[PDB]
Structure formats: structure tokens, C-alpha cells
Image (spheres, grey):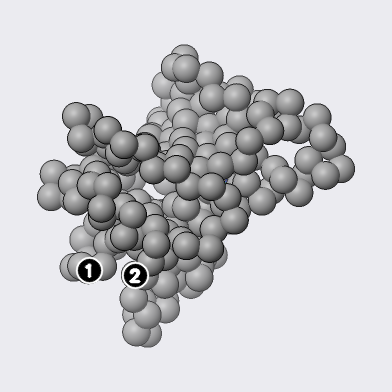
């Protein structure tokens, strides 16, 4: 298990998301589904010039898996996945500019729901989750598990769990007062409101 410090701007953003009073928390789901859709668009585009990129799985979809027993909401996709370099360095380096722009926009009157306009929508997961675990598999790398409960650090390890084939699974370990996001009616309402035109099948698993 390797432990890393977040980029300073990202730790600041995470603290702002955790500490700001903001009732419209449901937007985290739209952000995470949008991110999955982007990863799916990426593998679909790459597979046009290299069909072998789909040898790890032809189906392009998103599954939403609430679990009342573990108090987790899992968002699974069969997108392009992420390399170890993406998890440790690349995505966080890119997120520095968007984080700075988003925090400046909030000071000027923007609200937390606008987070996706800055390329840092993933961090809205901390509106509802005390911990986030991300399992990912890219065709050019091994399967990894990234994890953070904020506090300024995250961990990365090789994942020994069940192989995924290709894609990303975001596991949200929900805060005790955010269990509404495990209810079928609530998740259906949010998907219909914010993600009705996503161009991939979204299957909401029943418990
Ligand atoms: C270290 C930071 C990790 C944060 N992390 C987990 C997320 O951001 C995130 N959340 N849900 C996701 C679903 C996914 O399939 C993927 C994924 O596999 N790829 C390739 C991906 C990468 C970047 C993006 N952005 C989209 C917005 O603009 C920045 C890049 C969209 C997809 C990433 C997801």
C-alpha cells in the first residue's frame, strides 16, 4: 500500500466540499455518471482504429449498485479505465487548474452544482461519501485500487479482488445521514432529472 499527499489545491477543494453548507448534494451522481460516460466515449473512439482494444470486453455500459448492508453506492462502467500514472499523477496534475478556477468562481457567486464546468466533478463524491474507493483496469496496465477518506492523503495498491476486465468502479462509502442515495426511488428520480440523455445503458441493480 502506497500513501500519497494530494496536490495542495485538491486537498483545499476536498475540505471546501466537506465543510460548506450546501443542501443540493444529489448532483454528485450526475458528475460520476458523466465521468463514466466520458471513459466509455474514449474506449469507443479508440476501438474504431484498434478493434483489439475491446478484447477486454465489448459491452459499453454503466451499472448503479446500491448496498444497504455495506452502506455503499457503487458506480461501475466498462470505459477505458485508468493507469497507475493517471491515479497517482496525471489526473491530479490536470485538476490543479480547474480546482483553482472553481474555487475562484465560488468566491464570485458560483455554487457547488457548477463543479463539472471546471473538470473536477469527481470530488463532489465527498458531498455524500466519508470514503471513496476506486477500482480501475486499463488495457495497458494492472488492476489498481485507489482510496481516500480525504484528510489530505490517498492510497494506491494493486487490487487482488475480482478482475474487472476493463473499466472503473467507484465505491461510495456513504455518510450515515446520506442513505437516501441507496433508495431505488431516489436514484431513479436523480438519473431521470440529470442523466436522462446519457448515451449508454444505465442499469440500476435491485437489492
Ligand atoms: C485520480 C483521480 C481519479 C478520479 N476519478 C475516479 C474520476 O474522476 C472518476 N469518476 N468517475 C469515473 C469513471 C471513470 O470511468 C473514470 C475513468 O476511467 N476515466 C478514464 C476518466 C478519467 C477522467 C475523467 N475526467 C472527466 C472530467 O474531466 C476530467 C477528466 C473521466 C473519466 C474516472 C472517473
Toward which corner of the image does residue 73 lie, by quadrant? top left
Name the residue carrying label 1: 22
Question: Residue 56, relative to residue 41: is it above or below?
Answer: above
Q: Residues within 10 Å of mark 2 (few under 14, many from 20)?
A: many
Residue most extreme to the top: 160
Counting from the top left corner in percent of width and height, residue 204 is at 39, 43
Asked whether, in this view, residue 174 is left or right of residue 4, the answer is: left
Toward which corner of the image does residue 82 lie, by quadrant? top right
Residue most extreme to the bottom: 108
- Report helix, strand or loop for mark 1: loop
* Quadrant in the picture for the N terminus: top left
Toward which corner of the image does residue 121 lie, by quadrant? bottom left
Name the residue carrying label 2: 112
* Quadrant in the picture for the C terminus: top left
Counting from the top left corner in percent of width and height, residue 165 is at 60, 24
Front residue of 170 and 104: 170
Question: Residue 118, relative to residue 48: is it above or below?
Answer: below
How many numbered badges does the structure rendering display? 2
- Can residue 5 be seen in this snapshot? no
Question: Residue 103, relative to residue 78: is it above or below?
Answer: below
**Disc 2 within 8 angstroms of ligand 1 (CB):** no
Counting from the top left corner in percent of width and height, residue 87 is at 53, 39
Question: Residue 167, relative to residue 175: is it above or below?
Answer: above
Q: CA distance from mark 2 to mark 1?
A: 8 Å
Asked whether, in this view, residue 95 is left or right of residue 115, the answer is: right
- Report helix, strand or loop for mark 2: helix
Residue sitting at 39 percent across and 62 percent down? 192
Residue sitting at 31 percent across and 36 percent down? 206
Counting from the top left corner in percent of width and height, residue 148 is at 35, 38
**Disc 1 within 8 angstroms of ligand 1 (CB):** no
Residue sitting at 42 percent across and 78 percent down? 105
Residue sitting at 51 percent across and 68 percent down? 118
Amino acid at each position: 500500500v502506497e500513501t500519497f499527499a494530494f496536490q495542495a489545491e485538491i486537498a483545499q477543494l476536498m475540505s471546501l466540499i466537506i465543510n460548506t453548507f450546501y443542501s443540493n448534494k444529489e448532483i454528485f451522481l450526475r458528475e460520476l455518471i458523466s465521468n463514466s460516460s466520458d471513459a466509455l466515449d474514449k474506449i469507443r473512439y479508440e476501438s474504431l482504429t484498434d478493434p483489439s482494444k475491446l478484447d477486454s470486453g465489448k459491452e459499453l455500459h454503466i451499472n448503479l449498485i446500491p448496498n444497504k448492508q455495506d452502506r455503499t453506492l457503487t458506480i461501475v462502467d466498462t470505459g477505458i479505465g485508468m493507469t497507475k500514472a493517471d491515479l497517482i499523477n496525471n489526473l491530479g496534475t490536470i485538476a490543479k487548474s480547474g480546482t483553482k478556477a472553481f474555487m475562484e468562481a465560488l468566491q464570485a457567486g458560483a455554487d457547488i452544482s457548477m463543479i463539472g464546468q471546471f473538470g473536477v466533478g469527481f470530488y463532489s463524491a465527498y458531498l455524500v461519501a466519508e470514503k471513496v474507493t476506486v477500482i480501475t483496469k486499463h488495457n495497458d496496465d494492472e488492476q489498481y485500487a485507489w482510496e481516500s477518506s480525504a484528510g489530505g492523503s490517498f492510497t494506491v495498491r494493486t487490487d487482488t479482488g475480482e478482475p474487472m476486465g476493463r473499466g472503473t468502479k467507484v465505491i461510495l462509502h456513504l455518510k450515515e445521514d446520506q442513505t437516501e442515495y441507496l433508495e431505488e426511488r431516489r436514484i431513479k428520480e436523480i438519473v431521470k432529472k440529470h442523466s436522462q440523455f446519457i448515451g449508454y445503458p444505465i442499469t440500476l441493480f435491485v437489492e
